[PDB]
């Protein structure tokens, strides 16, 4: 059922790498080198995703060669997603998906590993893995490997629910959405491209884990809200809330924006707590998190990926300013880390 999106609140300014044209050229030449398409129409659709632009908005100060290298990960993701999930009217079986997806996880870890059957664009996954990780630090490569595996595992969970034709509970959605969207992998690629790496102490600290998870969750709720209208021409926050509260998709909208603002409000409180004492690496991650929030909104409605959904405008204030913890025990612990 059709929904009316509400305006988005974001207290950060738009930002974009001033060498975007060069970044996009490197990416289009790479798309053609590895032929990440079966026909000219697929090629045009892949370029129209503007994966280089969203990374360039997240990395406005990074070397354009390195922004191009990490954007290959997103172009590969889009190309492979469109292929694997458009493979017949019958939903992909988890038991068929799992043996393929662990092979892709292995190639992200160690591209010298090869298999008796490989899907198209596996050569491209090897190439982008070497391009991204060869120049990185050992610590950055360890983060790349763990976050890629977590995203592949999360994709598996989405396949499980699609096979069952079922909708997860709101608590289970709020636990897993950060994994199904791969935002930890996104953050790992920001570190590699921009040249930062958290200390083990910071990365493990419960306040920084709450910062990363709250940011990952609200960013992917924005993704869900932008992709709904287009997805309706066929596990979205709208569908999950509608089932949870036994209400219509339109009735779910104010609930979705309340959850969005409460999680982004918590993110801002943790940001305010951590910035004063933050070292150069945590400062760089927080900057990347701010730029990603704007990047999703500024690219999401102009990109051909997600008109089906007109930009609903900018909110002069958040939709929900309550500082109280959300009543979802998978994520309620985040509110314990506020100083």
Image (cartoon, rainbow, N blue to C red):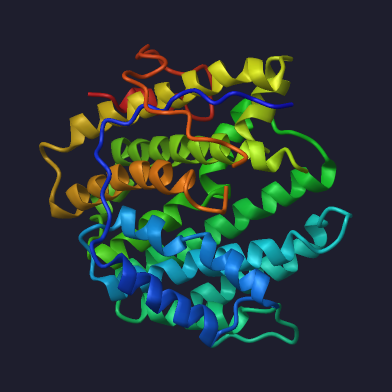
Q: Nearer the viewer, residue 159 or 63?
A: 63
Taking the spot 35% from the left edge, 14% from the top edge, the residue there is: 323
Taking the spot 65% from the left edge, 61% from the top edge, the residue there is: 81
Residue 299: horizontal and vertical position, in percent?
43, 49
Residue 115 seen anywhere in this rendered image of the structure = yes
Taking the spot 64% from the left edge, 54% from the top edge, the residue there is: 155
| Vertical relation: 281 (above or below) 83 | above
Q: Is residue 19 left or right of residue 45?
A: left
Q: Nearer the viewer, residue 121 or 13?
A: 13
Residue 16: horizontal and vertical position, in percent?
28, 55
Q: Quadrant of residue 3?
A: top right
Q: Nearer the viewer, residue 88 or 4?
A: 4
Residue 40: horizontal and vertical position, in percent?
65, 76
Q: Is residue 41 left or right of residue 331?
A: right
Taking the spot 35% from the left edge, 81% from the top edge, the residue there is: 134
Residue 320: horizontal and vertical position, in percent?
41, 14
Q: Is residue 118 left or right of residue 187?
A: right
Query: In which quadrant of the rendered image does the C terminus lie?
Result: top left
| Vertical relation: 13 (above or below) 102 | above
Q: Residue furthest front?
A: 307
Q: Residue furthest left?
A: 276
Total marks shown come to 0
| Vertical relation: 36 (above or below) 190 | below
Residue 137 seen anywhere in this rendered image of the structure = no
Query: In which quadrant of the rendered image does the N terminus lie?
Result: top right
Q: Is residue 299 left or right of residue 255?
A: left
Q: Nearer the viewer, residue 174 or 334?
A: 174
């Amino acid at each position: 059922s059709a929904i009316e999106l509400l305006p988005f609140h974001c207290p950060f300014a738009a930002a974009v790498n001033p060498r975007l044209a060069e970044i996009e050229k490197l990416c289009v030449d790479w798309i053609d080198e590895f032929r990440l398409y079966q026909d000219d129409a697929q090629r045009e659709r892949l370029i129209a995703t503007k994966a280089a632009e969203v990374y360039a908005r997240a990395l406005p100060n990074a070397a354009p060669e390195r922004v191009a290298d990490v954007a290959k990960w997103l172009y590969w993701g889009f190309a492979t997603d469109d292929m694997v999930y458009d493979n017949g009217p019958v939903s992909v079986r988890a038991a068929d998906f799992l043996p393929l997806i662990v092979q892709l996880a292995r190639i992200a870890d160690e591209p010298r590993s090869r298999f008796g059957f490989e899907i198209p664009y596996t050569d491209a996954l090897r190439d982008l893995t070497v391009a991204i990780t060869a120049p990185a630090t050992p610590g950055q490569r360890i983060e790349w490997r763990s976050t890629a595996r977590a995203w592949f595992f999360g994709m598996s969970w989405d396949v499980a629910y699609a096979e069952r034709g079922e909708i997860p509970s709101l608590n289970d959605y709020l636990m897993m959405r950060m994994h199904t969207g791969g935002l930890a992998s996104w953050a790992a690629t920001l570190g590699i491209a921009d040249g930062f790496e958290l200390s083990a102490r910071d990365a493990d600290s419960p306040a920084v884990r709450a910062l990363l998870e709250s940011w990952s969750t609200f960013a992917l709720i924005i993704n869900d809200l932008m992709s709904y209208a287009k997805e309706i021409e066929n596990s979205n926050i709208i569908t999950v809330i509608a089932r949870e509260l036994s209400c219509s998709p339109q009735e779910a909208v104010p609930h979705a924006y309340s959850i969005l603002d409460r999680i982004s409000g918590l993110f801002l409180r943790l940001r305010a707590d951590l910035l004063p004492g933050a070292d150069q690496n945590l400062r760089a991650l927080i900057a990347g998190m701010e730029h990603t929030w704007r990047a999703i909104l500024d690219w999401g409605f102009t990109s051909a990926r997600y008109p089906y959904q007109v930009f609903p405008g900018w909110a002069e204030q958040p939709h929900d300013t309550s500082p109280d913890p959300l009543p979802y025990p998978a994520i309620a612990w985040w509110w314990e880390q506020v100083a």
